[PDB]
Amino acid sequence: AFADAQTRKLTPEERSAVENYLESLTQVLQVPGPTGASAAPISLALNAESNNVMMLTHAITRYGISTDDPNKWRYYLDSVEVHLPPFWEQYINDENTVELIHTDSLPLVISLNGHTLQE
Image (cartoon, rainbow, N blue to C red; front, side, top):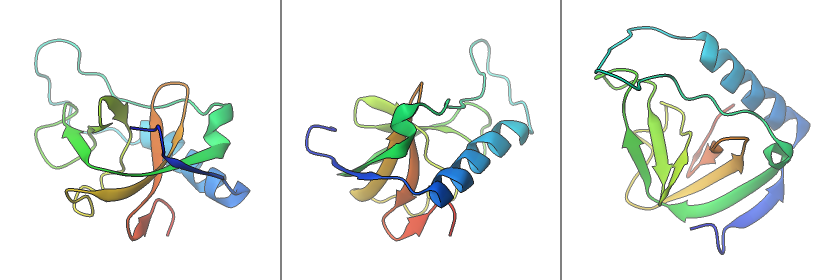
């Protein structure tokens, strides 16, 4: 999926807001919504790649777990797991322009077709 994905350097401003979003994200937790076992949050750790943004047109999958209501959930880019902010769930169509940086876990989608994490 990331064989031909574009690439670009992330600005300090975009890196600050994002890191601010991911960091504040873990802090914002509500409605447990237990479903048996294995249902913990999903926060990615910023790595050296956190600077190199990856751009690709791909359909984002939505795998909910934190709750059974349109909220903080796990997304998937192709056969990989990704972090798509809850505000793009509606901005995500069949094929979308997804710009994400690969963290220590999964790639954080900093931007989307006609939208951004810190607009």
